[PDB]
Image (tube, rainbow, N blue to C red; front, side, top):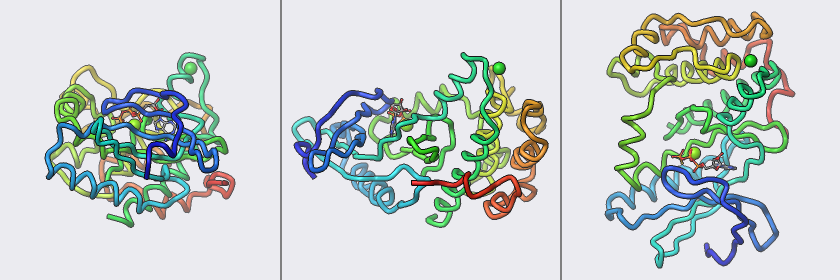
Length: 271
Ligand SMILES: Nc1ncnc2c1ncn2[C@@H]1O[C@H](COP(=O)(O)OP(=O)(O)OP(O)(O)=S)[C@@H](O)[C@H]1O
Ligand SMILES: [Cl-]
Ligand SMILES: [Mg+2]
């Protein structure tokens, strides 16, 4: 409700659309974050749509989705603050970067935790069909081995210049063949993207790489990639390989994934 209700501790990071800061809620000393967004250049139309997105965001209550908490406006700076759950383990990009630097592969048990809890996150997103971009940077870890989807697509609308540069410069490593060939909404497309993510978690590189977009498109089109490292079981390799099937209808559904014998209770969330 009010900015005075919170005490900024420090800046965790400057995103493309503003700062993310670690904050303490005064009422109870609860540690949270907020996302600092300047809406000064927005039209009335863009702000109502922003309001719409926030309302849908607050409507997501799931252990495996970064939890929404509050909205605060300081009109003096034309700054909107979105209070979110603090995820102490950081994002998966950093984890993958750390794995490369230290020359160490991630435990299969970890990959199974992400697989399980991210699939559950997806099942929830689909039920409510909404931003579900599954890049490692959009995936967070708390302090209890819980995995949370935190795609803050919301913020694109604030600066169209930065949003255009992000869309044009960036390489869609996780782009499904359907979505490349002029497609739209299909939940099997999200399964392919999850496959890419789990693959990158295992191999520390995405399944398809190129220096060019049309070279990347050729690679994806062919649907060939290296097997994930041999430290990972044939079972985990078969499931990931399955999510990366050229045909969306050959990819496993959320339900089919969760039926896999690899996935056990301890792989799910515990708060
Ligand atoms: N809920 C959260 N809990 C803890 N840390 C977070 C949370 N959200 C973001 N971070 C971290 O804060 C830093 C800033 O990133 P963000 O501004 O959230 O997004 P960004 O990737 O920089 O920009 P985007 O994706 O366009 S919103 C990153 O290092 C994140 O790992
Ligand atoms: Cl290595
Ligand atoms: Mg982000």
